[PDB]
Amino acid sequence: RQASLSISV
Amino acid sequence: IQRTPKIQVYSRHPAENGKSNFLNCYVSGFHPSDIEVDLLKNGERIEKVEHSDLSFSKDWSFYLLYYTEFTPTEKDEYACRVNHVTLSQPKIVKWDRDM
Amino acid sequence: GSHSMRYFFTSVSRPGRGEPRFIAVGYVDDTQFVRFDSDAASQRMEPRAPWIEQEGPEYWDGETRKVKAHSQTHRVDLGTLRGYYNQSEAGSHTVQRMYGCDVGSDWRFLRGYHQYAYDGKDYIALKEDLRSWTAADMAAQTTKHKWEAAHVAEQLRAYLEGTCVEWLRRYLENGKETLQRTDAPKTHMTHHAVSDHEATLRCWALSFYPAEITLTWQRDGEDQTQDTELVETRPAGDGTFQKWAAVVVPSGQEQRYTCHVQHEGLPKPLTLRW
Image 1 (cartoon, rainbow over the protein chains, first blue to last red):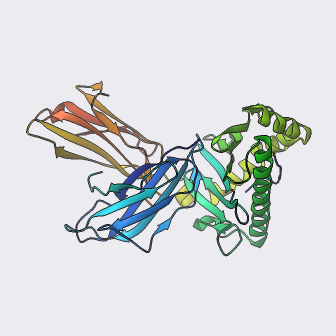
Image 2 (tube, each protein chain N blue to C red):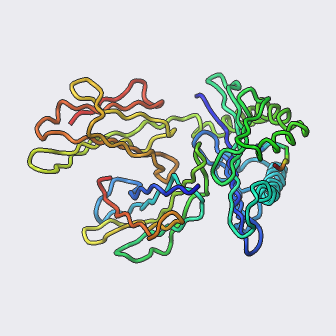
């Protein structure tokens, strides 16, 4: 199951 | 950074003339991921070729497996033909049943 | 046994027309179990092993939403990095991310990782403490300060020691019949004469799982390195792996040479001789 997190550099 | 592909051409099962099998072309160690890979029978392109989903190693370099059903024989030559940005001319690696 | 779960994400920009090509894959140990390809028809996270298929509609909905969001994150990243590196908008570039967790024999947490690359070089990586960042250059330093301010390492540390590990155990249970089974290498030696006074011996290991393996040659009970060749481990195409090692020997001295095979599926190492 994927990580519940969404981030850009 | 551009890294040239390593290439292995080989059969899924030990090869026996006239007995069906799977022809594999494994490309790895390359960057960027855009790449063209064909399987050849007597220098011609085989049409029903499939491949794995793109993935990569620890050092970030890519790998892919191209494959198709085939039947080894005494007369047919099999090969994998690879082009990539790092190569100035397509590289042809011949299938050798001993490797 | 001892185990891992890993996700891999690649986006490649397409200057000229449209959105990047995006490809995501998930693995338990050496077994692919899910995939997403932005070029496919479904536009869904898809199953790739029998044991994941029993997950219900809410799993597939959730994993689809998460992977499509990931794809959009990558797309924004490709724009940001082009700026940071003062690069033209005419060329194609790549972003890669890998993350996941290992557990020991007791299925308890051993380590976690989360790392990013731009154009095939290290960009930013979470350290082993799951608290700190390794930034390779001054662009990555900017990103490190941004992720400090957004509590990113905190969230990663919680996933990696928690959800990552809990769902890995679940998969290990549901896929017991294949995932907890070791397939020992089927081994044999071939002989290829090169002349009237020399020959190649090739030691084969076939149809094994997991991929980890060691093949070594000895001469008269001592390790031999001169005149050997060792190919990279390669997929058979049916979920198993292949490898071989070869040595050139004086014809008639074949006996002195032994091939030694180490693999998790073998109680004790194998020895082969011609």
